[PDB]
Image 1 (cartoon, rainbow, N blue to C red):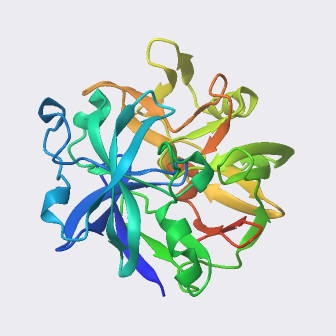
Image 2: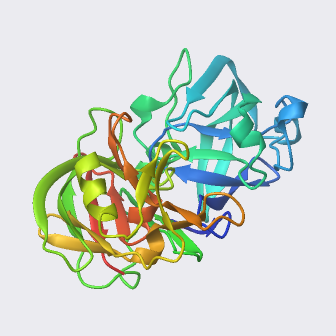
Length: 330
């Protein structure tokens, strides 16, 4: 089997991407944030504290003839950005782009933190990291991909995120028309539950490539590119007037700037992030200070190849017995 679904930016900045997901019988379609950095499929629901729901579409398990309470199961998750959610668990039928999993754990939110409430466009998350990170207790549950894998034509999914435009998540096949050149594959460590890999270096603009190992995670659920402070300083030093602002929470730059590109290495291959991808617009409405899309990972504890990086590539998440990651230009 295969599946193919379009993923759409939630706003004009590509702050996140939503993908329609069918849950239950009859189908209830919710727009979920596909997140290769976590492993829970959770939704706003009829059980979510009413004051914490503000415009989201909810899953109502009592209206699904295939929903079953997973007795005694609870979940609770905290994300890198400080947000969180928790609740109880159903199993139900879940379909993405024509690919169906029966008995998928659907984690129903009883509580969500303010940032989720305040984002009316995101109805929940669909985790695509390794199932070892799944938070359901006392019986850990599998991700949608893990459940689908054996049925897929090939045990893979691909992320093809757009810049200010829709893109695609495919399951079970590689669309050879969706990228240019070849796909370069690179080793993955699953030791921390992530799609963790090592970039071979970077360049800023038309500058020379610096060969240096950068361990990090391919994370579709993180907006920005978070890299070591040395790398980030080297990038922003090429932008007149850019500075790190403790008050704002990272590097800012004059909105009048033309940003240089940023290149990262995948083995001997190179992925070029155009400068415009690194612009996250005014820090507040009407400001001429703009927020940068490359930020320091210092004090996160891990480097994160988030959407800024991933949307410059066609990315293969290869879930073979020994997982790997593939990157192609597009």
